[PDB]
Amino acid sequence: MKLSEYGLQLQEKQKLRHMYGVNERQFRKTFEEAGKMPGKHGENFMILLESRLDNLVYRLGLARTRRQARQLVTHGHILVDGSRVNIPSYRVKPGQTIAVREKSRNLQVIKEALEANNYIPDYLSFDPEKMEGTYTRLPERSELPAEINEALIVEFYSR
Picture 1 (cartoon, one colour):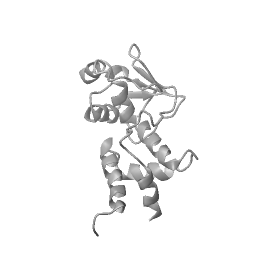
Picture 2: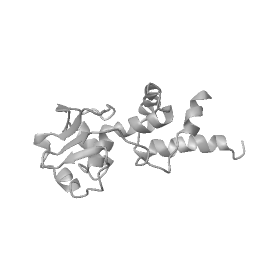
Picture 3: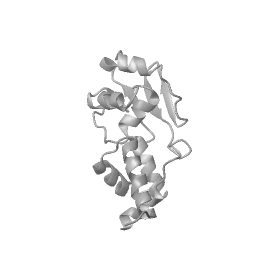
């Protein structure tokens, strides 16, 4: 009942869930769905989250914030590998790219986020000319939030 480490664990899970705003259904599911690769389930969880269609959009600088990258997806405006994906929970993987939709290119919210280029990761190749964000490699932890953890969340399911 008094302060204890058991709480700090479920805590790291909350703040993280509020980080990119991953719904619980996406948080728990994405987890058991990451237990597939033998690369430490923890890391795998921090990897799938990045695949978040919205994150990628807000990362390549196609939107100023999640409220901008979220509406862009749902409003069907991103062509993954050349395919519209109005699904925010879907997930992308190397061998495909994110390409804004033609009728959705002069969007001020985008033409406005292109300038807000807050540095683009090294595994993401962005071509402003065609507005194509290619996933050329997987994301490492060196870039993903460092003030975040996942072990305390690993055993959480063991409870």
